Length: 282
Length: 283
Image (tube, rainbow over all chains, first blue to last red; front, side, top):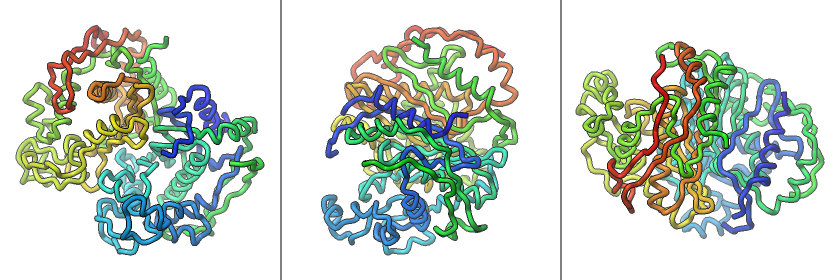
């Protein structure tokens, strides 16, 4: 079968061959509605035509599981991707003055384990408050794997205003058939250049983690896009990437048996056979 | 130009050749596939499937019902649409522990989530003004002020309210897109019976995309139907195979007889599907 990465690339071509020109501007070729499927059967979708910040992926996900909404908690691990939206300055440009530095608000972490609970600050303890979606999802996979209501949604219209940054991961569904676990992510906005690759890895990792705990095997991962765009700043770099030939995907391994989703630790994972192409500038 | 219904029948074809056996809530076998997407042009035509008639009166009347924010199945039944009565009956409500609800009270379903998301639900006769987020109107407001915005979502999945309604929303969420004065829409359906409900669904949001376009003075663009659990009942394989052989006829055309300016001002009499001739029934 066709190397999975070809889909991501097959899309970049489309965004350019049919994307229409159009915050902070910077320009962008957009497209509306796309879907790519990546296999998780004895392989992990970690694009090779360009290196992917695996540590960021793995370290950020574990950060969501905890339900943490503190940018600092994640940066203290070396991943500074969420710091910008945590700086005292930014929080101010949003009206959030009483807000402590590092507080992102009811973002992913909060939505995943305390959906619906009234948000206060990153320190407050929301235990027993809200709906623990991540856990309910795991529980259903276990007792009713044929359920078509296994959905985890981070889009809370009532909390959007309090967020330092709106979700680009409205929701994701889980599917179980023949002992194989699949997941479909619905991204409202995707930066094909510096985001989608990270995103693919992010949710494919979650599927593995979930499949491990439910005692199932990973299947497919459907990445569905709403507004897929390319920033003109990447029109060149990417044009070079397309040149590159996709190398066989690496493999993910869970070095130890784990019971609860929270018990997962960074050291529990290993990426073997990851041979990505060089890195120019982007 | 390739006909639009070919995209639909194509998915039925995919399910047949690649779908696997999967049981539903009652134990009934179905042939399933996870993750699907289809695009339907809404430009000078309306995607109302023709290889099998679609209950248009039901689509149109049910949509109107959602916009009102109604959760009373009676209000819909009093229009000829009986698709929500079973879920609101006296017996079905008791068996769910809702013995204190008057007949017809569906719970915080679609209507409520669209106009009052997050509002504290009481009953189908309580007033929820100013309560909750009017996602519907917010969509219209955004399409007008910031057409390039890519956070124009209308989510009906409310984890908190799920255990208070008849059954979980089938239409998790939809997103609107605007480009070159055209309004495109994408729907995410978590579950869909390819031959029984998907058609009805395509017509619902195609019509909604027509109404929002009308109000914001834009032209209908495309409708992307993204499915999660696409399936067909096993005992429906044979009749479906017959339908597949049928040749799709030109999609009809929808018309807005008068000029409407508010989403809530739309009436059933304001619509007209001209040129609809679907194939005869099959079984």
